[PDB]
Image: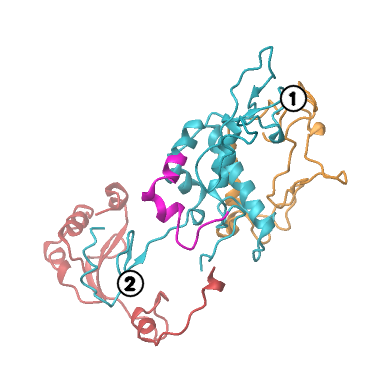
Amino acid sequence: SEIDSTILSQCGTLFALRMNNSSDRNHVLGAVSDSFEGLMGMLPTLRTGEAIIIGESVRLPMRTIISPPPFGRRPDSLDPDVTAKWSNNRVQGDYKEVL
Amino acid sequence: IHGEYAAAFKGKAKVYKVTPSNNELKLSIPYWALTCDEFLSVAFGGLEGSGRNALIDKIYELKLQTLKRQEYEGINEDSLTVDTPIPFSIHKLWFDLYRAEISTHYVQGSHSEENEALLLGEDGNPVQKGDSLKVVPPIYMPHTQAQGATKIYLSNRGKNIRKPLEGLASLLKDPRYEFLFNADDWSVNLDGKTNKDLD
Amino acid sequence: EISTHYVQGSHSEENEALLLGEDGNPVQKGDSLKVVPPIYMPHTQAQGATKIYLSNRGKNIRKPLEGLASLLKDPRYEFLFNADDWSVNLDGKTNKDLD
């Protein structure tokens, strides 16, 4: 719903995963030229990993299951683990180095 | 903001107030820990003319003097910017920048600091030599270089920042800004040395 | 915009009225690769001392220049101003090119 409508409307192919809110679903429906009511009515109830490929790169709009990547190759941001860091016992600090 | 969480945590959290009563600490934000822009916005009310440049130059000179007097790790005269958190005296800054605007020189033409024409008392001592820690300004002889008496000329180096300096003095004498200008342990002496550091 | 000409009327670069030391050398000559600015004698044309008049060629862009100087020394802009193999030295020479 934040992407510009004109830019989105010119995208060749859409990969609509599970969508929760209604505004985004309405925008996606308004930014597609091949609408099947049965397929587009299933958006808020898609499993984790399913997709609905719509556009000129496929013969028909179709509900697929994207093949999982090989084990050990999974995207992951190495953000700090709050629970693990906070569960550790506290140690005496030294803020002269920080200063 | 409303101070309503102090009672929720009886002894499980440190409380930093402005006016402590029994055991709560005191909130203290030293002014030299700020940047140049924030300090100007909070103290002088947002100067925009050449007075801002004059204040920046004075602050930089004071910081350079403080670095010269006191050793600091990894900081030299080449890698010191205005925003470096190095202590500097605000009272000395105000005293210099104000005395360079109202006091009169005893000799015309030049305004050397050694030719200060302070109005002396009957006994010989000056009436008001002025103080730095105290915000009282010194008294000077009237500006009149006519015939008959000695020729005394006004200061020839002052800027047009008398009003912001008066405002800064009023803030300095305000007991509501102690958490900035008169912090408990982070007070800055005349030579730029504090009891403790930012650590 | 800061350094003052030793003689009024003309703003020649060779007449830079810098602050000299007791030995004779200037207090701060100034560096280019480093961002230290040169030191200059105070502007004063009164009697007793020499006539020092500030340069009249200076523009009104002191604040943007100060901001750029602050940015140059910021270690967060190394990718922009201090590229490893694309660092431009004083005479405009690069170790490598965009290829």
Three-letter code for the amino acid on which mark 2 is drawn: Lys
Q: Can you tell which chain is drawn orange?
A: C
Neighbourhood count class around disc 1 (C-alpha, 10 Å): few under 14, some 14–19, many 20 upward? some
Residue C22: x, y in percent? Answer: 85, 45
Residue B192, located in which quarter of the rendered image?
bottom right
Three-letter code for the amino acid on which mark 1 is drawn: Gln
Q: Name the residue under label 1.
A: C45
Image quarter of the N terminus of chain A = bottom left
Q: Are marks 1 and 2 on the same chain?
A: no
Q: Which of B83 and C68 is in front in this view?
A: B83
Q: Can you tell which chain is drawn cyan?
A: B
Marks 1/2 in contact by CB < 8 Å: the verdict is no
Q: Can you tell which chain is drawn red?
A: A
Residue B185 lies left or right of residue C91; in this view the side is left
Subunit under mark 2: B
Residue B156: x, y in percent? Answer: 65, 26
B178 inside magenta stretch:
yes
| Colour logic | by chain
Q: Name the residue under label 2.
A: B14
Residue found at the very far right of the displayed protein: C23
Say what secondary structure mark 2 lies in. Answer: loop
Cα distance between the residues tagged 1 and 2: 59 Å
Residue A56, located in which quarter of the rendered image?
bottom left
Neighbourhood count class around disc 2 (C-alpha, 10 Å): few under 14, some 14–19, many 20 upward? few
